[PDB]
Image (cartoon, rainbow, N blue to C red; front, side, top):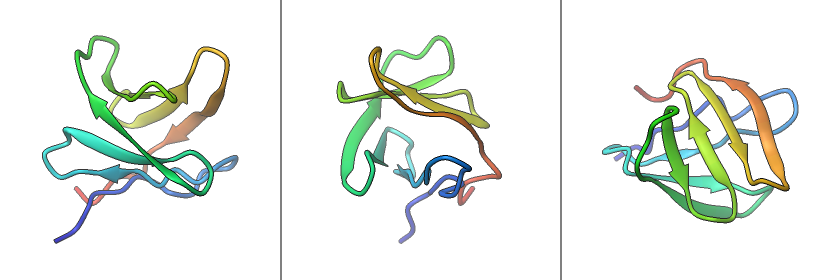
Length: 82
């Protein structure tokens, strides 16, 4: 049983995403606490959003922006678990 996870080590922030295997959900790190964002209607990529932040996964690029507070805007994923 393994959760998929992103690069988890970006220049600015650790992008430790808990990619749920069906990729229906991400448990994402605010800083040192985890929230849960989920993929809804994606158009610009794959959007995992909860409300706290809006996580946008382009597939290989991962950014996460609330429209007031972006926490990560430059992570380009090596590859997750898969």
